[PDB]
Image (cartoon, rainbow, N blue to C red; front, side, top):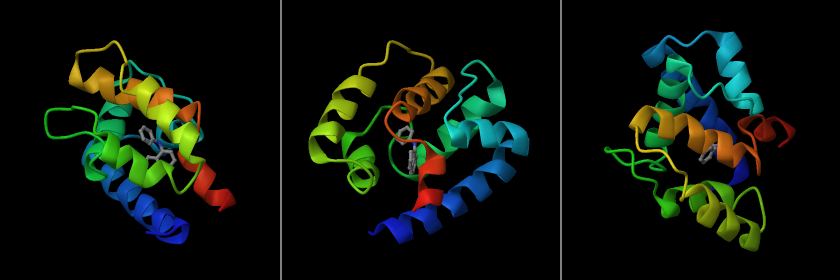
Length: 119
Ligand SMILES: c1ccc(Nc2cccc3ccccc23)cc1
């Protein structure tokens, strides 16, 4: 993968996850910009859908380091990715939906999805 292919792939996942979840564009924009309303159900589901589609979350919402590295190593330096994995893999949340939004919130501290528009 390259950054340009990530951009294309992410746009597609955002599109399909929007129709799967019914999230309003305004709330999708908030998520993409890194402002996560972690308790909003459609935000949770949108986050979950994108992360599952990238194999960052497995079917039972377990965080997968391989999946997050495949994406983040395109965007930030190796050592920063290591720290991101160690940080965001240890989020204190057991509920799958809330875990999904909290994971996007944690990671957004490092890079937001909107990042890919600044290629
Ligand atoms: C875990 C991994 C990534 C993200 N956010 C995002 C940051 C920037 C590019 C991305 C590409 C694919 C999926 C999420 C991306 C949130 C939680």
